Image (cartoon, rainbow, N blue to C red):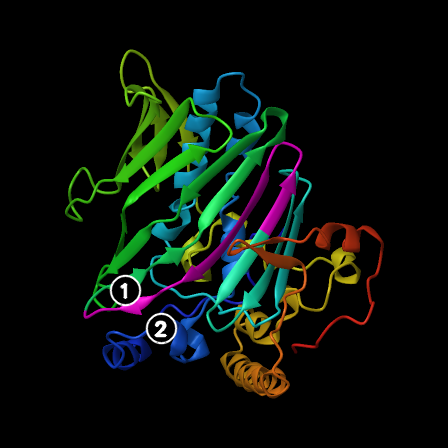
Amino acid sequence: RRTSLPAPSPSSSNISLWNILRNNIGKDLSKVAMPVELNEPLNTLQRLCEELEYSELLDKAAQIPSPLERMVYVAAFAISAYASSYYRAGSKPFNPVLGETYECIREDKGFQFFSEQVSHHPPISACHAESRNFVFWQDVRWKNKFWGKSMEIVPIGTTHVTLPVFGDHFEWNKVTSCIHNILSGQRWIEHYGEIVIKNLHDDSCYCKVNFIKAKYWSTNAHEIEGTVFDRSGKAVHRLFGKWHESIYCGGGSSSACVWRANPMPKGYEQYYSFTQFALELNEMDPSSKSLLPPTDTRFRPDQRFLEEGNLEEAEIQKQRIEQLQRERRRVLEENHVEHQPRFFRKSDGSWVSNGTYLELRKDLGFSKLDHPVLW
């Protein structure tokens, strides 16, 4: 897999953000159009993919007789979702096209990941991933707004992981993020709220993780404080460390480093500050190009022509795609059509896999009236 990118990143063309944001101080940024040079060659379905860069934590979890330690490893997996945002604090990803998909099949870590863009008004992304040790799925929409100085990220939705060999159902919240000084010199991100991890199927244990807010320069910057309590509210295991750096079991008589962020690629800054994991998800190999629907994001031109350094071709493709989506919003609006997304179905207000993607790839070369062209 390719540890480079066929062009370098725009180091900055963020004068644009100045007028575009201080002219939108309360507005849902999903509703505000922006020049493509402010994007990054990834989208929100792949950014949900990122949440499994450390999936192997789960690969250890279900392999432990102790429930509480399984919780501990889960809490580590949960926090690790935020680690990638330390270096990529600002940049917005591509808003997925309605109906778009993304597929990543990793034999390496042994999971199969698929994702679809299921609604555009509002923007909802649905992801499902299958592994022998866990199934990981969720459903999110972002309420991003820019106040005077800092930019807010508000994920809405919950995250579900099950461990079969133990029948474990872990469910926890996403949490808020202010990016302070997103226009000023040093963008520093900060996470707000409490993550609560519940086992639905196990009453024994529940986990609370808190983000310590501290002045940017404190020695407690980016600190976390976690506990795994029993039913009675008494503390069992404590987690400590920093959410971009390292997490630890223990804290008392003994301790262990349960998680460590991978190190960044060599001179990562010149390629949008991606993790190695990130550089590997809009990279397209020869053998897979004959196995996936034409709605996978690697096909998306403006994305690829930005990965390529062609600002003009990207800016062109992008307006083409967007006005096409207006036309089809309107085409199924006049036919009073409630669009239904392809391999996710809505239940109780969550988009879960209907159970069709993996097996509809199971047989080679699905060219079976590949449902609408998007580019």
Quarter occupied by the C terminus: bottom right
Q: Visible in this render: residue 266?
A: no
User: Of residues 232 and 12, which is closer to you in this image?
Assistant: 232
| Residue at numbered disc 1 | 151
Q: Tell me the tag on residue 25.
A: none
| Residue at numbered disc 2 | 29
Q: Position of residue 54 (x, y in %)?
A: 50, 39
Q: Position of residue 3 (x, y in %)?
A: 56, 52
Question: Type of residue at label 1?
Answer: Met
Q: Which residues are magenta?
A: 128-148
Labels 2 and 1: the sequence-earlier one:
2
Q: Visible in this render: residue 141?
A: yes
Residue 91 lies in quadrant: bottom left
Q: Taking 64 as reference, is 283 left or right?
A: right
Determine whether 214 is above or below 206 in the image. below
Q: Taking 224 as reference, is 44 left or right?
A: right
Determine whether 167 is above or below 328 in the image. above
Q: Taking 136 as reference, is 356 left or right?
A: right
User: Of residues 110 and 350, which is closer to you in this image?
Assistant: 350
Task: Determine if the magenta segment contains residue 144.
Answer: yes
Q: CA distance from mark 2 to mark 1?
A: 10 Å
